[PDB]
Length: 241
Length: 233
Ligand SMILES: OC[C@H]1O[C@@H](O[C@H]2[C@H](O)[C@@H](O)[C@H](O[C@@H]3[C@@H](O)[C@H](O)O[C@H](CO)[C@H]3O)O[C@@H]2CO)[C@H](O)[C@@H](O)[C@@H]1O
Ligand SMILES: OC[C@H]1O[C@@H](O[C@H]2[C@H](O)[C@@H](O)[C@H](O[C@@H]3[C@@H](O)[C@H](O)O[C@H](CO)[C@H]3O)O[C@@H]2CO)[C@H](O)[C@@H](O)[C@@H]1O
Ligand SMILES: [Ca+2]
Ligand SMILES: [Ca+2]
Image 1 (cartoon, protein in one colour):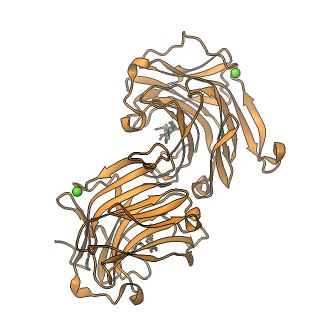
Image 2: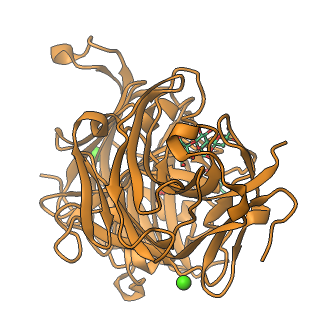
Image 3: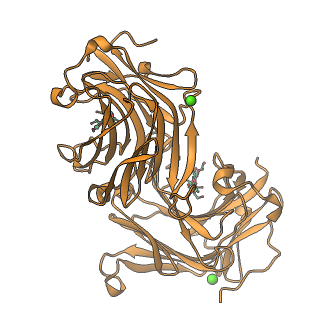
C-alpha cells in the first residue's frame, strides 16, 4: 500500500542466548535503515507483554557509524539505550563483520572482532525468553533520526556474505570465551528451512517489506530497497576480498 | 484513602543517559515535596532488583533550597547521598531552570546553568539500566525531613513551563557539550503519547496521586496538591 519496497530476512526459529555474526556491507542513503538485530517476535503486540530486542542500525544519513540499542519495557512504553559507534571504512563502502553476543549477564557488540559496546545488567536482565536473528532494509518517516528520504539514490542494496550463529557455552569457547560455533550460512542459496522473507510493514516505516526483494547471487544474500513495483537486481555483487 | 490529593507526571519511555531540563516554579509549604527526578520504574519492587534514581526535591520547610540525591542499593536497603543546595530566589517565588545530566561517569545537577553538585563514580557506577523523567507533588509523614504539614497553605501548585530532553552524544554534542537536544514540550497541551499521570501512593506519602491534579493551562503543565475533593482552580 506504501510507495516503496524494502526487505527483511529472519530465522524461522528463535533462541535463548548466543553469539551472532554477519559479514556484510550496508546500504545507506538519507532516510534509510540498514540493520541486523535480535528480535523476540510478538514484542509489537500491545497486550502488556514485554519487548525484547537488540539492535545494530546504520542510519542512512550517517554511514560512518552505526547505532546500537537494546529495547526492553513494552509497546507504548519502551526503554531504550541508543548509542553511536564509528566504523571505518563507512558501512556502505566496505564489508565488516558485525557481532552480537547475548547472555543472561551481558550483551556485547563487535565490529571485525573488536568490541565497540558491552552492556551489563540493567536492560540485559529483562531480555527474557527467545529472540530470532533478523536483518531488514527500509526507510523511516522520522527525518530527525535518519534524515529526509532521498528517493533518487534508489535502488539500494545490502549484501550479506555469510552468517554464523553460536551457542552460549560460558567459559568453554576458544581461549575461555563464552561461545561455540553452531551453524554457518555462506548464502550460496536461500535456505527456506532456516530463513523466512518478510512481507509486512509497521507504523513509521515508509516502505512495504517484500519477499520480492530478497535473493542470493554470487554467494551472497541481498536485501533490496526499491520503488514500489521496481524490484530487481541487474547490477553486480561487490567482492569481499 | 488519604485525605489529600497529589500529582505525578512521568514519561512513558525510559532511556540510558542524557540531559534533562525543566523550566519550573516549585510548590512549597512545610511538610511538602515538590520535585524533578530520574526514575527506573520497578525500583520499588523488593524482589532483589536494584534501585535506580536521581532526585531534586524541594522540601517545603525550606523553599530557599532543594535536596539532591542518588538512590542505589535496593528496596528495604537503600544507599543514599542526600545533600542540600541553596536556591535564590526561593524555588516557590520564581522560575528556575533545573538540569540533570546523567552519563556513565557522573551525574550533574544545575540551577540556571550553574552547577550545584557533581558526583563522579560511586553511586553513579550503580545507576544501571534506564530511567524515565518524572515530577511529583506530595507530602511526607516524616516531620524531621519536611516539617509538620501546614495544611492552611493548600491548595499548592507546581508549574512547569517547558521540558527539554537531550540524548547523550559524547564528542558529537551541541554547544560544546556531550548532549544533543532530542525533544521539547512547551506544554501548550498535554501529550498523552509522551506523558503519563500518576494514580497511586506509597508509604510515607500522606497523599494520593491522581490525574485530577495534573493539567495544562496557558502553555504550562500544572501539578496541584489539594485536600481530597477540592482539585481545581
Ligand atoms: O507490524 C506487524 C509485523 O510486525 C513484525 O515485527 C516488527 C515490529 O512491528 C517493528 O516494531 C520492529 O521494528 C524494529 C524497531 O523496534 C527497532 O528500533 O529497529 C529495528 C531495525 O530497523 C526495527 O526492525 O520490526 C519488527 C520486524 O520487522 C512481526 O515480526 C510480524 O510478524 C508482524 O506481522
Ligand atoms: O507504590 C506503587 C507505585 O510505585 C511507583 O513508584 C514510586 C515509588 O513507590 C516511591 O517509593 C518513589 O518515591 C520517590 C522517592 O524514592 C524519592 O526520594 O523522591 C521521589 C520524589 O519526591 C519519590 O517519588 O516514587 C515512585 C514514583 O511515584 C511506581 O512508579 C508505580 O508504577 C507503582 O504503582
Ligand atoms: Ca558467501
Ligand atoms: Ca510553556
